[PDB]
Amino acid sequence: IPVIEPLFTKVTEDIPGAEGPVFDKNGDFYIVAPEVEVNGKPAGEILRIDLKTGKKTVICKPEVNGYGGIPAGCQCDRDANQLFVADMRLGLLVVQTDGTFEEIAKKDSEGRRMQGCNDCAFDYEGNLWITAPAGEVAPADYTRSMQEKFGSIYCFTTDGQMIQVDTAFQFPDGIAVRHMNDGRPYQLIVAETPTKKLWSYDIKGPAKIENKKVWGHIPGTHEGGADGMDFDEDNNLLVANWGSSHIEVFGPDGGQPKMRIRCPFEKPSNLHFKPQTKTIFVTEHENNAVWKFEWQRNGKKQYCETLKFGIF
Ligand SMILES: [Ca+2]
Ligand SMILES: [Ca+2]
């Protein structure tokens, strides 16, 4: 498989478990530090990074009834400048730029206790697809589906339902939505980390997925596997392969990667394009740091970059 070796430029440092890179509607850049702990208990953080200086500001250190969060992944909303954050202890949070936040769900649409979440992806219809590799949210004792298949997938819909849409994954992690050129969502891709697979479904409608399939194969026998992912503007899927020192690039039909991108570190965890550029910001756990590099083309627009009131 062809491998390219772009120049990685350091962005910021010392972010425990650096994850969830995201740009808001003002172009501000955020990351989460899920692994910050106080007295051995979770005290994860959501940070804003000043791209000019690399200086970090913690805007939110979420805790619910004394249970601190493990915020792990993010998406920016479209209609309001607020971040939806998947948290391994707290489930799904909505966080404002002022640092205030709310916890969205203690239970799902069927009254089942909510599971801790890892990453999420808005489709263009505004529905939010979320991976949930942890067990029940706080105050339940923390567990994760790395050994046993209890990880779930949710769709948090525009009408505010938190719908469990699949179950029994061994650590579902990255997630992405592919759209038709006319903007209709039609495929969901979900990383199952340790099994070295990417799974696909057909999106039939809000919270409606069918035709589960093993869509892609992640290279390697290292400990780790697919972590975060995102599409570029031609619908190639770029996937951080934690432990492999590469980001894998899959073409629109999946299968094996068509190209790999060598990183100067073994553990890329997640990535995000900066809007209107070819720049991909990458979080990684070898150094607990953030970097950026130039890809071959622009990212596929995120939901936050689209317009509610477009004409075209
Ligand atoms: Ca992740
Ligand atoms: Ca991303």
Image: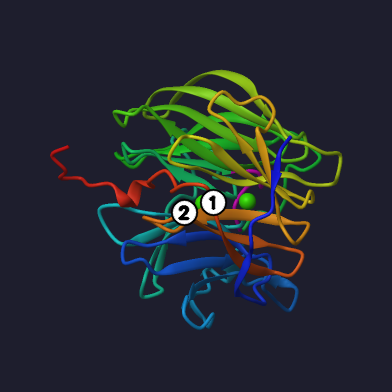
**Residue 211 coordinates in the image, percent (x, y):** 54, 16
Residue positioned 51% across, 83% down in the render: 53
Residue positioned 72% across, 41% down in the render: 193
Q: Which residue is mark 1?
A: 295
Residue positioned 42% across, 43% down in the render: 300
**Residue 24 coordinates in the image, percent (x, y):** 37, 62
Residue type, label 1: Trp
How far apart, in angstroms, are the residues tagged by discs 1 and 2?
A: 5 Å
Ligand 2 is within 8 Å of the C-beta of the residue at disc 2: no
> Would residue 228 appear left or right of 100 to someone viewing this image?
right
**Label 1 element class:** loop
Badge 2 crowding class, 10 Å Cα cut-off, few under 14, some 14 to 19, many 20 or more, is some
Badge 1 crowding class, 10 Å Cα cut-off, few under 14, some 14 to 19, many 20 or more, is some
Q: Nearer the viewer, residue 128 or 141?
A: 128
Q: Nearer the viewer, residue 46 or 302?
A: 302
Q: Which residue is mark 2?
A: 278
**Label 2 element class:** loop
Q: Nearer the viewer, residue 175 or 67?
A: 175
- Magenta residues, start to end: 132-138
> Would residue 141 appear left or right of 98 to someone viewing this image?
right
Magenta segment, prevailing SS (helix, strand or loop): loop
**Residue 90 coordinates in the image, percent (x, y):** 55, 57
Residue type, label 2: Lys
**Is label 1 in contact with label 2 (beta carbons under 8 Å)?**
yes
Q: Is residue 216 magenta?
A: no
Sooner in the amino-acid sequence: mark 1 or mark 2: 2
> Would residue 127 appear left or right of 137 to someone viewing this image?
left
Q: Determine the image quadrant of residue 10.
A: bottom right
Q: Is residue 135 magenta?
A: yes
